[PDB]
Image 1: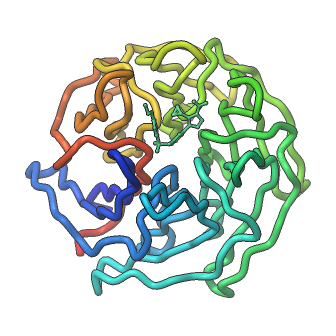
Image 2: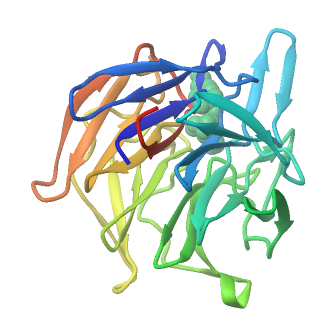
Length: 288
Ligand SMILES: CCCc1ccc(S(=O)(=O)Nc2cccc(-n3ncc(C(=O)O)c3C3CC3)c2)cc1
C-alpha cells in the first residue's frame, strides 16, 4: 500500500481517531472517526479495505467490550459495520491468511479467551476454529508462510513468554519455542522470515527490548532495542521496515513513532502522532 493507518486508542478514555501517516512526505491525515470509540482493538487489511476488530469502549458512560468488526474504505472515507464476532474481544490479536481474518484471544470482562475465530469477507460470516492451548489477552499475532502465530499475553493470572502456532489444514495449535522475555501487550509483526516481538509488559516494567523468532532455526534472538520503553503499542511493516506507534512507557502515553531498519539494526524516530495514546490498531493500505 502507501499509508500507515492508526485507528482508535486510549488517552484518558477510548478514542475514535482514524489517522493516516505517509512515510514518503511525513504528513498526517485525520480521517473519518470510528463509529464507536475503542481501545485494545486490532487492525488489518484485506483487499485494500481496512478492518478494525474487537477492543473496548472505556467511557464515562461505562465500559463495554467489543465484538465488533468494522470496515473502512479509503476510496469513500466511510466505515461500514460487518458481522460481529461470537464474543467480545478486548486486547485482541488478529492475523490475515488467504483473505480471511483470524481473531485471537482477548478478554470479555474477567473472561480471558483462548478461543479463535475466522472471518470470511466474501460471506460476511465468522466461524470458530480450534482454540489456542493458552488463554491470551494482549496477545501478539502474526502470519508467516500462511501459519498463524500467537505470542505472549496474559492468561488471567500470569504474563507469558510462551508462543504457539496454528496450522490451518490440521486445525491445530502447537507450542513453539518460548521467548527469552515475558511480554504482554507487545507489538508483534513479521519481517522477512522472522516474527518480531517488540516491547510489552513483563509484570514489572514496560519493555524497550525487541526479539525475533526464526521459523527455520526455531530460535529467538534479541536485536537492537527501541529508544523508548513502551507497552500496548501499535506495530506494522512498511517498505521492509518496522514502525511502532505510541504506547505507554510508565509515565506518558507516547506520541512517538519509531522505525526499525533491519539492515543497520537501528531504530530511529520518524514522526509524532497528533497526540499520545496507547492500544491503537494499525495497518497499511492505499491513500484515500
Ligand atoms: C496507567 C494505564 C496503563 C494503560 C496501558 C494501556 C491501556 S490500553 O487501553 O492500550 N489497553 C491495552 C491494549 C493492549 C494490550 C493491553 N494489555 N493486555 C495485557 C496487558 C498486561 O499488562 O498484561 C496489557 C497492558 C500492558 C498493556 C492493554 C490502558 C491503560
